Amino acid sequence: MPDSGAVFTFGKSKFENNPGKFWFKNDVPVHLSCGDEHSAVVTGNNKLYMFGSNNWGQLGLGSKSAISKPTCVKALKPEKVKLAACGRNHTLVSTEGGNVYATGGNNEGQLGLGDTEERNTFHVISFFTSEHKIKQLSAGSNTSAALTEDGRLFMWGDNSEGQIGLKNVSNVCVPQQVTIGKPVSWISCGYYHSAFVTTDGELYVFGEPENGKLGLPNQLLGNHRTPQLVSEIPEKVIQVACGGEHTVVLTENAVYTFGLGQFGQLGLGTFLFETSEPKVIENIRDQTISYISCGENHTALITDIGLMYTFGDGRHGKLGLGLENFTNHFIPTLCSNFLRFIVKLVACGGCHMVVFAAPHR
């Protein structure tokens, strides 16, 4: 409706799960995050809006089972919210003043609060201060990450499969630095694996050595609890996004995928259902990709000119393609319904996807 655009919801986001649309009065989204069954929107006026499932208190809005409509977390209004990350049952938020907050499930210490007690309102992670300028947050299944502007990566929560790169420790309930001796520029926590990109463009992956999603050859899979270089991508890596059983990697002129693709989430065609080796998506070679996003079982790409391509599991309409079109897509497919829009932001969750797009005029 407004020229600045709208947030579009697809799938089971709880906003009656039909393709939905909302916007804010004199405010605009600047950041989107989707967890397994919930969503977060950070606005330009530095407010946080939460919606979806709240069974574990992941919305930070009290004890209600679910909240259908995007709801302002007014408890954080004294602070300038800049970023948010949604995991399976928890949410992380960072503020301009140097405070990082968490709410939701805490069974593996993913809130980073020093215990394993669940919370249903946002609590300060006292480990983080104004000394830590947060560039990025990420959150997986009972896992958490915060990346600073000067390239320090901190992770906490579950490490039972090595998914926070802390070797033989089972889990941690306090943020701990994860490093291989280089500044980090990008981090993504998938469900049971994670990855980071160094400032020199190297990709490191760690976590569950299953389904080929680490993208490492067999001789390296034993050391999956330590971050290891994906040497089979020779080009400089810019972004990584980790999903349920797949991984998506952005380089300057190519998108790589690896792991499981039984729903089409690898985008490598109708014949390739899994790969342990990183493979380039060939159908979109002609276009430059500016952003990548992973849900549990689907993938979204935004191009430099603001087109969006999706692929993978079509259930609930989460690919954002068509009202009746619920089939799986094995190649990146143009979101033709956004053709007269610039797609600006996208986040993908378990059974839903959230999109920020503004119309061409």
Image: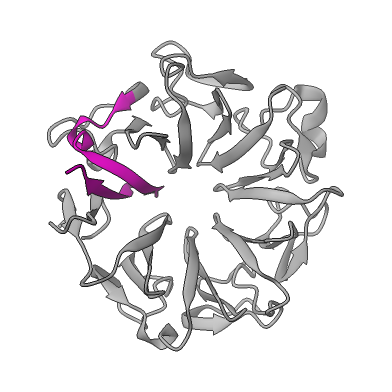
Which region shows up in magenta? Answer: 333-361
Query: Split into 4 quadrants, where in the image is the C terminus?
Result: top left
Q: Position of residue 198 (x, y in %)?
A: 73, 44
Q: Position of residue 259 (x, y in %)?
A: 56, 28
Q: In the picture shown, does residue 279 fall above or below 92?
A: above
The residue under the point 17% across, 33% down is: 322
Image quadrant of residue 94?
Answer: bottom right
Our reading of the magenta stretch's main secondary structure is strand
Along the line of sight, the residue nearer the viewer: 253 or 69: 253
Magenta residue check for 336: yes
Along the line of sight, the residue nearer the viewer: 207 or 93: 93
Residue at the right extreme? 181
Q: Position of residue 42 (x, y in %)?
A: 40, 67
Q: In the picture shown, does residue 355 fall above or below 229?
A: below
Q: In the picture shown, does residue 24 fall above or below 260?
A: below
Q: Position of residue 29 (x, y in %)?
A: 34, 62
Q: In this orientation, does residue 11 appear? A: no
Q: Is residue 285 left or right of residue 133?
A: left
Magenta residue check for 269: no
Image quadrant of residue 213?
Answer: top right
